[PDB]
Image (cartoon, coloured by chain):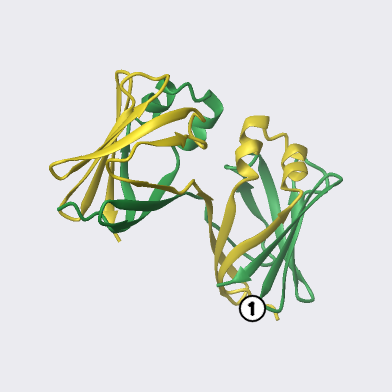
Chain colours: A green, B yellow
């Protein structure tokens, strides 16, 4: 069949590394790229193709219980070992990440259909907002 | 509410760059990371949290018609300008990507519920397989 319509989920990817090196794609970005899974969404009508690609990366699972300190290795970020404590302040879930970096942590809470997350390291603050699907 | 169960899709991400630099995450990987969208899937039962994170990147749309050569800029790969021609060989969709790199192209076809894709540059071959969702 010539019909390639649909949603296609990558299951295998062999020698992506050598193909990328042959294209002179720099080392640091090859290192990340070979970790990705791709999903392809093909819209085919006759000899007209349109298709969208999305590269995805599954980060680490983190599970914990509020009030019980745990060890965390922040792979896929800076890869340091921190001692994380998670508590409630009212509605606000607060985590202190004891380790080399001072003032390292985050705060998480709901307002409406929005989830707010502020991540802090040193003097630096990163603010993220998510919508509920 | 303390109930943070659900699927949450990132809509905003501010000063991710400075937070990452404060964590001494190297330049090349910050450059990619600030392009990602995150989806969080939270499973909360009482004071027990489990959550999965997935970082995604939307690649470029490519649309073309078989038999009509077109210009392609391969952003999010090597960012070169190629002249791409797409033809059918039997069931097999064949693309030749005329440009600086010799023997640059790919071949795409269906066998079963699998989509096969081979990408070639120079002497190097990359083979990918997708399953139909």
> Is A66 drawn above or below residue A45 in the view shown?
below
Q: Residue at x 47, y 36 (%)?
A: A33
Give residue A22's quadrant in the image. top left
Which x, y percent locates residue A111? Answer: 73, 76
Give residue A81's quadrant in the image. top right
In the displayed structure image, the side of residue B51 where residue B70 appears, left or right: left
Give residue A80's quadrant in the image. top right
Q: Is residue A100 visible?
A: no
Quadrant showing the C terminus of chain B: bottom left
Figure label count? 1
Q: Which residue is mark 1?
A: B3
Alpha-carbon neighbours of circle 1 within 10 Å: few (<14), some, or many (≥20)? few
Camera-nearest residue between A84 and A114? A114
Q: Residue at x 35, y 36 (%)?
A: B69
In the displayed structure image, the side of residue B33 where residue B54 appears, left or right: left
In the displayed structure image, the side of residue A130 where residue A127 appears, left or right: right
Q: Residue at x 49, y 25 (%)?
A: A25
Which x, y percent locates residue B41? Answer: 53, 65
In the displayed structure image, the side of residue B100 where residue B57 appears, left or right: right
Residue most extreme to the right: A123
Which x, y percent locates residue B50? Answer: 54, 64
Residue most extreme to the bottom: B1
Which x, y percent locates residue B42? Answer: 56, 68
Q: Is residue A110 visible?
A: yes
| Mark 1 element type | loop
Chain to which the residue tagged by mark 1 belongs? B
Camera-nearest residue between B99 and B77? B99
């Amino acid at each position: 069949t010539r019909d390639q319509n649909g949603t296609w989920e990558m299951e295998s990817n062999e020698n992506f590394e050598g193909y990328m090196k042959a294209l002179d794609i720099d080392f640091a970005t090859r290192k990340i790229a070979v970790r990705l899974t791709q999903t392809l969404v093909i819209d085919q009508d006759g000899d007209n193709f349109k298709w969208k690609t999305t590269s995805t990366f599954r980060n680490y699972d983190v599970d914990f219980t509020v009030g019980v300190e745990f060890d965390e290795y922040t792979k896929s970020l800076d890869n340091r070992h921190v001692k994380a404590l998670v508590t409630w302040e009212g509605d606000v879930l607060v985590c202190v990440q004891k380790g080399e970096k001072e003032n390292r942590g985050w705060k998480k809470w709901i307002e409406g259909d929005k989830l707010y997350l502020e991540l802090t390291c040193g003097d630096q603050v990163c603010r993220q907002v998510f919508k509920k699907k």
